Length: 489
Image 1 (tube, rainbow, N blue to C red):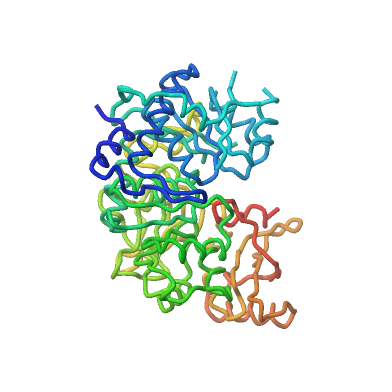
Image 2: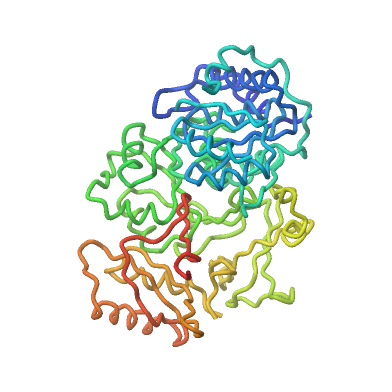
């Protein structure tokens, strides 16, 4: 009745010859994407992996990953798409928790994944971007004749949110393309899209797979780490019309001596998620490039963006409005309504909500509240209806939004990026700002004092940071999120 891979294959039957993917080694057409995926569905059956059993993907951003993911979906096998920058012990946990029957690993990750497997019938398959080779297994297979007999509400894949196995359906993919990508982003057949966010991050999964494939667009994939220069290369070479980033990437792009000219690129719309986008970055980016960045929030639990700025109605500094098809509510600790201007807990209702966390009743019952998901984010609503992010519940200072303070700090000309956390020095919690300075500025007690004064002049007295620590970089997840817990510890 419904299989997301089979659905895409049918959608794109008329454009078999159009390039679907460009990556570091070449181009792959829609025809080839379907062929190689359906052959991989056969290879899985031949390897003994049944429908509903999980495979673990530890794969770089190459056409192999969408082949593996879509080939698994067509087989009814449940791919679990993993972060590629984790430790062997991290992978041990994912292998054991997922009960993965096979793990497909990029050549560069083979050592970590092999080590993980040795601490334990999971089979290793190796993708080149002695174990069986992914490409060889697919070559040896015939394309599977029919998709598994799945429906809209059948479990299709997991992403990790110990990490929590976040369980998604076939329909959840479809809803993200239908509610967010088409209406908000305006993604179209003739687009060429490029996500700096990797396919293992929910954000990147939609950006570089769900969305372009849903409309017959072309997607650019990149295996290497997303530095400003690596990003610039694909922006210029393949002239994508859509680029998807995160605030730390935009910040560092803007200060690069290598920043491409307006005429060197073709971007018509950009997105940003993960952390909130500072007003000045959006303004300066649009001044230089001519296109807007749409700041949006999504989550692994909601599979993509559910609250976003809209093209032509950008309110830089806010997360915009609910994406139509999604409802959001703010509640206080007691579950009562939140007056505008106050910070409350975000709850989300929409049709892309995950089913559960796998093998975890306590966290599932605390998060998946029937029609509503408890997000873990803190939000405020303005007079004009726009939502403003206060930070994660865990990062709140005590009553103070770390984000409100960070957004003020980065307005100072010396500051490239900032994180604001509460640090307990026995046994008093003090507000501390960690500041990355622009290259033209040197760290000093004078400058630290100037920055404190800068914030004190702009916010209520209980908000300004008590210490400023100058750092070369902030600690960040692979995904570009700031690890404020590290700064606290």
